[PDB]
Image: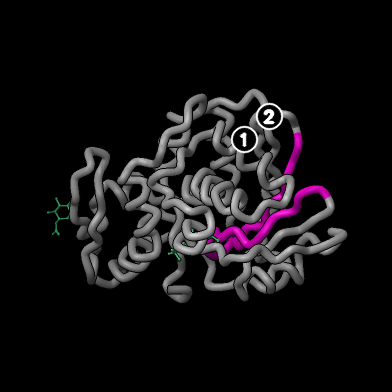
Amino acid sequence: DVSFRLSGADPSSYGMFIKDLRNALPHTEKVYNIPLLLPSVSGAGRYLLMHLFNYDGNTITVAVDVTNVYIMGYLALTTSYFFNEPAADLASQYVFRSARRKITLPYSGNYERLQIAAGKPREKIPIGLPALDTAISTLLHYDSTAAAGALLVLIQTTAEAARFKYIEQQIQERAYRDEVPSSATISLENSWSGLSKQIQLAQGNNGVFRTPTVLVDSKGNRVQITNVTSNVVTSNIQLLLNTKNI
Ligand SMILES: Nc1ccn([C@@H]2O[C@H](COP(=O)(O)O)[C@@H](O)[C@H]2O)c(=O)n1
Ligand SMILES: *[C@@H]1O[C@H](CO)[C@@H](O)[C@H](O)[C@H]1NC(C)=O
């Protein structure tokens, strides 16, 4: 398992958490020095438990699929909550079984559905460590509309930060003040599958992407990433979604 406590949290302790999160995900191979997530894992081993504590020390446990870093569901006191999707229902067979009741959330975990439930796109939702404290607090007591927004914050401040060093750094900048994600942040989130694919396709293509990936950079400018020498590949991305799952 991995843990993170908002009480006394700073950019350093958050960095240690994201490091732990990455290191908890198994791999047998690196592609261009980036860990390649496994095609599949059977049984309970598929799910990582993240213990998150709000400033007041109240806690939720979040179940994460270690093959794609997708959040499946979470436990809050004696109630488990899972996304309305087949992968999450499968997860509910293995994690939080001792919960007194299980609620299936009225949406899947994908960004489009969460934004619909939350009533706003995540371009408009501030993120940061204070926002994560709020998210944990919200998830402690069921409120599906509020939970959608909280989960958008949760996913970006954990999974997306694990996937991209840039995103980790953006959250570190928001340690004591929330701010909506940069356009570059949104771009990287939306491009993770594509980038993972092209980095793997480059393996037998002399480091060249079969299809270029369009990204927005730190200056709001639209760049085109075409091979593994790009900083996004050498610097930024920390985990690759296996092409078998794409
Ligand atoms: N169970 C799920 C499903 C999706 N997600 C996140 O939501 C995204 C899906 O968004 P779209 O369907 O809008 O592409 C994924 O990239 C993933 O990071 C998640 O964190 N947990
Ligand atoms: C590869 O990407 C680098 C970095 O963006 C770029 O400068 C260069 O033009 C590209 N080279 C090839 C052969 O695609």
Please determine whether, in this image, residue 146 is positioned above or below residue 211: above
Colour logic? one colour
Q: Residue at x 42, y 34 (%)?
A: 179
- For disc 1, the neighbor class at 10 Å (few under 14, some 14 to 19, many from 20) is many
Please determine whether, in this image, residue 218 is positioned above or below residue 72: above
Q: Residue at x 70, y 66 (%)?
A: 104
Quarter holding residue 201: bottom left
Magenta part mainly helix, strand or loop?
A: strand
Asked whether residue 206 appears in the rendered view, the answer is no
- Mark 1: which amino acid? Asp
The disc at residue 55 is 2
The mark that comes first in sequence, 2 or 1, is 2
- Mark 2: which amino acid? Tyr
Please determine whether, in this image, residue 26 is positioned above or below residue 220: below
- Quadrant that contains the C terminus: bottom left
- Counting from the top left corner in percent of width and height, residue 31 is at 39, 61
Would the CB of label 1 be found within 8 Å of ligand 1?
Answer: no
Secondary element type, mark 2: loop
Between the residue at mark 2 and the residue at mark 1, the CA separation in whole angstroms equals 6 Å
Residue placed under numbered mark 1 in the picture: 133
Secondary element type, mark 1: helix
Confirm whether the magenta stretch covers residue 70: yes
The disc at residue 224 is none
Horizontal side of 179 relative to 72 (left or right) equals: left
Please give the range of residues in magenta: 58-77
Q: Are marks 2 and 1 in contact (CB under 8 Å)?
A: yes
- Counting from the top left corner in percent of width and height, residue 200 is at 35, 67
